[PDB]
Image (cartoon, rainbow, N blue to C red; front, side):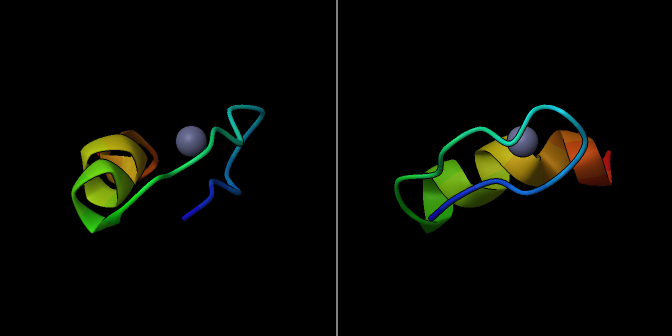
Length: 27
Ligand SMILES: [Zn+2]
């Protein structure tokens, strides 16, 4: 998918990698 939080704005590939990442912006 894609990130859009803070200055991280990283890149997401799929749902698994989607939450496995944004999980921080969420905690
Ligand atoms: Zn991010």
